[PDB]
Amino acid sequence: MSGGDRFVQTLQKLNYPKGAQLDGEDFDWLFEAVDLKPFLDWFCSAASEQNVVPDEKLQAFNTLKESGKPVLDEKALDEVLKTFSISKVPAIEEVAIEKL
Amino acid sequence: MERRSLAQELKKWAVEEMGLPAQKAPSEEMLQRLFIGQCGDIWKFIIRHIHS
């Protein structure tokens, strides 16, 4: 597998919008540079689908930051999320006057 | 001037955000080569959408 084909596959995994049109052979030259090769190899190993934040979530998070609400650190999130039963506890539809 | 700046952002992204040991990080001069042609748009994407 030519270094270039690996790179293009990684990009597809990372949901790059123009990734389907890219031919691997066009990037084989990037791996010929003895000095950059270690970095590119690293990148193609380190970057997976779990690392990808869609533009929507990033915008939403920036909005959250801008909203002046404190961004909970990982420890705090862990504490609070524990308290979260996966189970679809239907959003307590606040007993909509309708429910009452 | 634009290539040099992106090369710095990529370095920062690689070292600060993805945790690449500073010692293994290619020289800014060397990273500038990655922003040649169509590769430039790709790495811009990577810096923006790919996080730890």
Image (cartoon, rainbow, N blue to C red):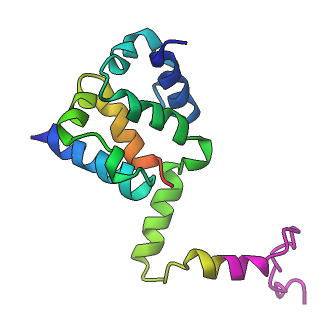
Give me the residue at 50% from left, 30% from top. A11
In this picture, residue B43 sits left or right of residue A91: left
Q: Position of residue B21 (x, y in %)?
A: 39, 52
In this picture, residue A54 sits left or right of residue B22: right
Task: Report the residue that reaches farthest toward the top.
Answer: A25
Q: Nearer the viewer, residue A60 or A99?
A: A60
Q: Position of residue B20 (x, y in %)?
A: 41, 50
Give me the residue at 48% from left, 31% from top. A17
Give me the residue at 83% from left, 88% from top. A97
The image quadrant where one finds the N terminus of chain B is top left
Main SS of residues in magenta: loop
Q: Position of residue B19 (x, y in %)?
A: 44, 55
Q: Which residues are magenta?
A: A78-100
Q: Is residue A93 magenta?
A: yes
In this picture, residue B12 sits left or right of residue A17: left
In this picture, residue A13 sits left or right of residue B51: right
**Quadrant of the image occupied by residue A48:** top right
